[PDB]
Image (cartoon, helix red, strand yellow):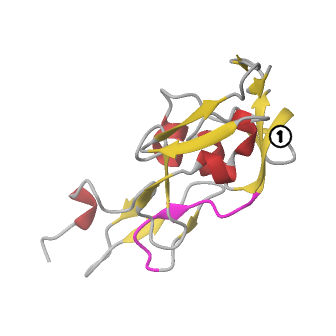
């Protein structure tokens, strides 16, 4: 009775909780929809990921979270800008910070695999997925353009 679940930190991941009599509700911000078990909000659209303003594509048909919670800079068509790291937009979009996205079904944070989803981050080179991150080794005689993410 006296209970308002919204007062609990965790209630409604990336969402706005509204306390109802015996439970509560999660209203999802724009572009987010409630997950199946209704514990949070996710963006299940698929789009391209870009390294600049959209240009320099590094990922295809990938989720905005996987794009922007990573090194991506813009996403989808029409080109949307990844929110900046100190924003609320980013708090919601990247609830686990840099390197992770929420599972569309369970909303559980998982390590984004740039190697698979964002192959662009290492064009012409070997991509090695790691915890919350990944590496890149350019083949002998070629070097990584830290700006184009291309080997040489």
Q: Name which residue lies at 83% across and 38% down.
A: 57
Residue 126, visible in the rendered structure: yes
Relative to 103, say whether 117 is above or below. above
Measured as percent of width and height from the top left, residue 35 is found at: 51, 72
Relative to 132, say whether 8 is above or below. below
Q: Is residue 91 left or right of residue 138?
A: left
* Magenta region includes residue 145: no
Region rendered in magenta? 37-46
* Magenta region includes residue 44: yes
Residue 54, visible in the rendered structure: no
Question: Of 21 and 61, which appears nearest the observer?
Answer: 61
Question: Of 126 and 35, which appears nearest the observer?
Answer: 126
Q: Quickly name the residue at label 1.
A: 79
Measured as percent of width and height from the top left, residue 33 is found at: 59, 66
Q: In this view, does 144 lie to the left or right of 86?
A: right
Measured as percent of width and height from the top left, residue 53 is found at: 80, 26
Measured as percent of width and height from the top left, residue 78 is found at: 87, 45
Q: Is residue 122 left or right of residue 32?
A: right
Q: How many marks?
A: 1
- The dominant secondary structure in magenta is loop
In which image quadrant can residue 106 be found? bottom left
The N terminus sits in image quarter: bottom left
């Amino acid at each position: 009775t006296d209970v308002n679940e919204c007062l609990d930190p965790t209630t409604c991941i990336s969402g706005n909780c509204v306390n109802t009599p015996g439970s509560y509700i999660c209203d999802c911000p724009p572009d987010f929809e409630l997950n199946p078990t209704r514990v949070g909000c996710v963006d299940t659209r698929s789009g391209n990921c870009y390294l600049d303003i959209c240009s320099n594509e590094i990922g295809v048909g990938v989720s905005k979270a996987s794009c922007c919670c990573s090194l991506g800079k813009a996403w989808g068509t029409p080109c949307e800008m990844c929110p900046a790291v100190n924003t609320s937009e980013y708090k919601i979009l990247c609830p686990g910070g840099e390197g992770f996205r929420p599972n569309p079904i369970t909303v559980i944070l998982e390590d984004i695999d740039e190697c698979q989803e964002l192959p662009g981050l290492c064009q012409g080179g070997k991509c090695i997925n790691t915890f919350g991150s990944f590496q890149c080794r350019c083949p002998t005689g070629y070097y990584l353009n830290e700006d184009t993410r291309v080997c040489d």
